[PDB]
Amino acid sequence: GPAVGIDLGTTYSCVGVFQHGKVEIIANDQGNRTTPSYVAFTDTERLIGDAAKNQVAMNPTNTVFDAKRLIGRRFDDAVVQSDMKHWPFMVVNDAGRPKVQVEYKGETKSFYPEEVSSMVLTKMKEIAEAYLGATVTNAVVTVPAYFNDSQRQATKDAGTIAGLNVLRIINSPTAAAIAYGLDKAVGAERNVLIFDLGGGTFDVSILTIEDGIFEVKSTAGDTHLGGEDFDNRMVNHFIAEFKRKHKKDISENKRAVRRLRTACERAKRTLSSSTQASIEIDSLYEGIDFYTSITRARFEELNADLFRGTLDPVEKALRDAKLDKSQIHDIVLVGGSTRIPKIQKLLQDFFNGKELNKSINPDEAVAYGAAVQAAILS
Ligand SMILES: Nc1ncnc2c1ncn2[C@@H]1O[C@H](COP(=O)(O)OP(=O)(O)O)[C@@H](O)[C@H]1O
Ligand SMILES: [Cl-]
Ligand SMILES: [Cl-]
Ligand SMILES: [K+]
Ligand SMILES: [Mg+2]
Image (tube, rainbow, N blue to C red; front, side, top):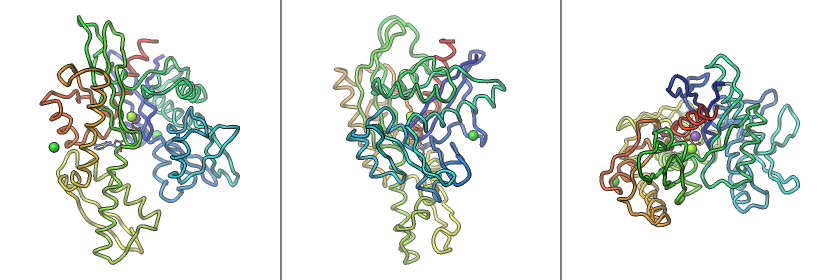
C-alpha cells in the first residue's frame, strides 16, 4: 500500500499509482512515462528498459525484446517457430519450453519468458518506488483479452518473481474502459470498442458493460502490426534516399539500419504533433552524416495501406459481436500509435464523425486503469 497498476506491454511498459482520487503515471529515471520492455546482457552488466534499448544497435544478439510473444507458450507452438526466425537473439528448447539464450559475463545463459518479463516488471516496480519513496508490493498487471490460462499464469509468475504480489491479472481493454470511468453503473448496458494499436500489435475489442461487469463480445486485430511497422516503411524510404544522394547502400550494416530506425521512430512521434520532422544522424555510414527531413503527408503515404487496413478488424469485431457501428456507445484509443492523426481520421470517418475518447495518453490508458483497479482491490 499503495498498490500499483502496471501495463506490461509487448514493446513498452507503463506503471501508474492512484492517490487522492487521481492517477499518477510515473516517469522513469530518464523522465519517460513509458519504458521499453527490453533487457540486455553484456560482458559486465545486465541492462533493463531505456539503458537496454539505447544499446540495441551495437549488441543485437544479447538484447532481448518481445518476450511477451513467447510468454506462456510451448516451443512447438507455431507462432513461436515463426517469430524465432525474425529475432536477432536465440530461442532454445528446454523440455518443450522456449528460453532465450544470451551471453552474460562471458558465459552462456538461458531465461524463461517470465524471467525476462520479471526483470521488466522489477524496473517498473523500482520506478514506482523511486516516486513513492516507499516499497511497492501489491500490483495489478494487464494482459491482452485473448491470453489463455498459461499466458495469464506466466504473466503472474513474472510478477511474483519481480517481488510483486499480483492482486489480479486483468484484460487491457477493460483497464482502458476503467480509466475513462466506463465501468460505472448508468442504467442499461453499454457497448465499448477499444482500438489498440501499439508498437508491435493491433487489438480491437468490443465490450458490453452492465452493472460494473464486463463482457468481451469480440476480439479482432493483427498480432504483427504496430508502430514498428510504420518505422520500417520510413527506414526503407530513407535507405533509398541515402542511396540516391550518396551512391551507397547501408542495408547490410545492421548498426546503421538500427540507428536509422531509431531516428525514424522519433521523427514519427514528432509528426503526430507537427507536419514535418528533421532527421539528423552523425556518421551513419562510412563517416557520412545523414541530415534530411520528412513531412506528415509523406509519412502517411508510406503507410497508407497499413493505416487503412486497421478498419478491417474493426468491421470484423462488430460483425462477430453482432453489432452495428451505431450501436457502439464509446470508442477508446489505446496504444501509442493511435496518437497518429491519420489513424484517428480513418477510425473517426469509419464511425461517421463519432467522437473518440482520447484525453488520456493512449499508451498510458491501460496502466491508468490498472492503477485505478489496484487501489480498489487494496
Ligand atoms: N506520439 C506518437 N505518435 C506515433 N506513435 C507513437 C507515439 N508515441 C508512441 N508511439 C508508438 O507506440 C508504440 C508502442 O507503445 P505502446 O505504448 O503502444 O506500447 P506496446 O507496443 O507495448 O503496447 C511504438 O511504435 C511507439 O513508437
Ligand atoms: Cl529507469
Ligand atoms: Cl483518410
Ligand atoms: K504498453
Ligand atoms: Mg499495449
